[PDB]
Amino acid sequence: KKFSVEEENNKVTLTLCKEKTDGTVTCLTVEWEYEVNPNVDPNDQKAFKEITILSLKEMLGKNFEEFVKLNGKKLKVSIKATITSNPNVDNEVRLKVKSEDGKIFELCDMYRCDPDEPCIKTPRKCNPNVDLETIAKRTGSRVVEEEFTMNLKVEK
Amino acid sequence: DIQMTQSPSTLSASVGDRVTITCRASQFISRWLAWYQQKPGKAPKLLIYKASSLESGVPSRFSGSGSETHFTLTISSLQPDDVATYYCQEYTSYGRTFGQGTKVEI
Amino acid sequence: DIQMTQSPSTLSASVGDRVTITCRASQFISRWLAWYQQKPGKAPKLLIYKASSLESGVPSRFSGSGSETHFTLTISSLQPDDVATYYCQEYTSYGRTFGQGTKVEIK
Amino acid sequence: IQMTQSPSTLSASVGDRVTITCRASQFISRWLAWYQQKPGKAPKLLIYKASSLESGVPSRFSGSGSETHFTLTISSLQPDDVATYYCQEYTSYGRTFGQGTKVEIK
Amino acid sequence: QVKLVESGGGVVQPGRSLRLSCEASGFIFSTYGMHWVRQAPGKGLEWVAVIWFDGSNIYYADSVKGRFTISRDNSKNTVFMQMDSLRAEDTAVYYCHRNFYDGSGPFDYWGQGTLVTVS
Amino acid sequence: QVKLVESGGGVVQPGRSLRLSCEASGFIFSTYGMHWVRQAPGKGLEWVAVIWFDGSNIYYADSVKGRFTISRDNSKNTVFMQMDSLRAEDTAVYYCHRNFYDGSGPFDYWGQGTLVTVS
Amino acid sequence: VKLVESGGGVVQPGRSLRLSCEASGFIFSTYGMHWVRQAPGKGLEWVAVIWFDGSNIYYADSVKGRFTISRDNSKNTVFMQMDSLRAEDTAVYYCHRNFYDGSGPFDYWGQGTLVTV
């Protein structure tokens, strides 16, 4: 379960690599880029990026073999979340990834993000029977949507 | 493995006020709990969502509830037509869990 | 820290009068203000959170308003049972602070 | 930069559904907002990120769009919805407005 | 209007199998999921299984796990449950159930149910 | 059934130590911290201190720094507070307070409180 | 939070004019501010942006080089100094502020004064 991350010019690399029983090693590589909007509080944007990385690591860890098969066209990534920089409030994150072959992967989770420290994964689970937008009204929060396209390739 | 328990399955009562039912969770379930009403001849109807709010068409005789691990239901006056089986339901995740339920009788 | 203040310390009114209480904050607290209500001899209870929405179980005549550094609480149609001390609370980070409080009194 | 809008002036009856458009010259990554103005008054924010409704605005107001093309919809006009509407880009330190559109009743 | 209609059931022998189905109408099953809820006589309600729209999120009650299977007809708003290896205490009315809170407009629908007995 | 209660109050002579605690039940102290809030008989609420569940996130009001210590009871859903070097100003009813927010809406709990006085 | 403008009134073509925004409800230190014009019968036009301390001072290209923008020291205000005014510059000016966070938007549109050339 080796991981590695690189960043340059607001572009990032995320890698997951595992040894095979065949005596060979193959790694999964993805890359994507993000923008920082000067009129939007950087503290929330910082948390969003870190959350994106954490959620992608979890998906890659669970479905490594499927992603080995998917050496090909860039995957579409969609994230919808309610994220605040306040330790007294739980954040909710939902991640969806769409394959070129039509396969869809989904995750959801909850996080706590202290403004000065790496985000903490929590034991609590997202409620699948309730629309997130409803939750945003009940506990006031801006709904944040973002999309990435990432290049999934495997080592040859 | 969320498990639910119930206040006594049978509540004999007069037509008067303050008939109560309680429900407990084995685990923290926040406020994601609902209550249902059933007559022997048909499928149950939803009365309460988030353990706090009326469904449309529900009579004003109503109650709110507790939180996290403990919940209640109260009837401010018992009508002869409110005689029914009542159930406690949990919906924090995929799938659902039901309590044993209770009966209110005149 | 963050300083919290309230403009009136006491308001006088008859039943059915409109009542407004304001609260001010130092620095910047976005919309993270809460309002609390206390009756004599009892622990305080949360009334409004997120400087806006009512916690369930309280009547619609209460409403919050304002943002950033200035906030308002208004009571339409004051009832004799609404007589209480009201407090302004901040929760932007670990720990909390409270304002001076305002009393609502009936003449 | 060069935001444009195609509806120009629209005319409608009370209660009619109204839709207006906006087009970017380039991809703007859904950094778009709408403003409402009435004569004699300063303009105010209506919708932000072209996807989320501002607080205090009635639910009939909504909007959505792609990185290159957007729409705004009012599900049913009220007499109070008569206004000039503007499309704005949020992608940088600077900002631009497109040619606005106008909605009038009869 | 929105309807859930159960089909199948009736008297079967111990062991073997029977197929139950829920036919939806008045809406498109494009989102969330569908549930089966059991009503044994003399007993309260209990949950049996769920199928989420994607068809990948499948869960079973522990009491029946490793027994029964859930599937969906891709061409129709219909959900199937196959029962097998039936035994005493599988006797019940089986109800089709759907629930989605949707903010101000919550949904809760139940069908008439169908009776399954073992003899 | 969610409760927090106070104990250990009473009259303390100047300069003497006192130990207070929040005994609690109906929940597990596993995700959010607890606060101490105090009220002088003639004045509004004042915040004293917070302890995060097993956290390093300990904060104090300026008026009590160096005189108070907050510590979790590792064996129980209980929070301890110690105070030292008390002065006449420290006359207040102390309350246990717990508060957090989630998608379900607000959670806010208070105990009955206890009276602590000096001389 | 209120924003108001100083200056304006009728000036002759080719003349200079100084305008300013004033604010008392906040300290202008965390996000930038904008100038917006509205010629009669026309929609809103963005003119310039200013940021706290060192600044991104982008000006609309259509009017560039005829004027500059600057923040005063304390006394929260923003100044703009125009020159070589033309008849086309007749407009109502507005103060504008805009930023976002997880709690949602802040706009605070001001009430300005009329400028006629």
Image: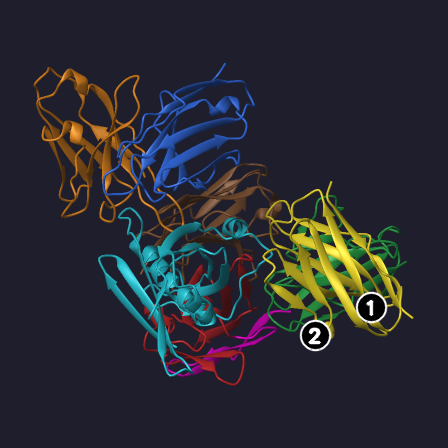
Chain colours: A cyan, B green, C brown, D blue, E yellow, F red, G orange
Q: Which residue is mark 2?
A: E66
Q: Amino acid at mark 1?
A: Ser
G20 displayed left or right of D9: left
The residue segment tinted magenta is: F1-29
Chain of the residue on which disc 2 is drawn:
E
Looking at the rendering, which quadrant does residue D68 occupy? top left
Report the front residue among B84 and D92: D92
Q: Amino acid at mark 2?
A: Gly
Mark 1 surroundings: few (<14), some (14-19) or many (≥20) residues within 10 A: some
Q: How many marks?
A: 2
C44 displayed left or right of G43: right
Report the front residue among C39 and A30: A30
Mark 2 falls on what kind of element? loop
Looking at the rendering, which quadrant does residue B100 occupy? bottom right
* Residue B11 sits above or below residue E106 on the image: below
Residue D105 lies, in percent from the top left, at 49, 17
Report the front residue among G24 and F112: G24
Residue B1 lies, in percent from the top left, at 64, 73
Residue D41 circle label? none
Chain of the residue on which disc 1 is drawn:
B
Mark 1 vs mark 2: tell me if same chain. Answer: no
Give the residue displayed 72% in from the left and 48% down from the top. Answer: E24
Q: Which residue is mark 1?
A: B9
Mark 1 falls on what kind of element? loop
Mark 2 surroundings: few (<14), some (14-19) or many (≥20) residues within 10 A: few
Q: Is residue A92 magenta?
A: no
Of all residues shown, which one is farthest toward the bottom?
F75
Q: CA distance from mark 1 to mark 2?
A: 32 Å
Q: The N terminus of chain D lies in which quarter of the figure?
A: top left
Residue G10 lies, in percent from the top left, at 16, 16
Residue E83 lies, in percent from the top left, at 77, 67
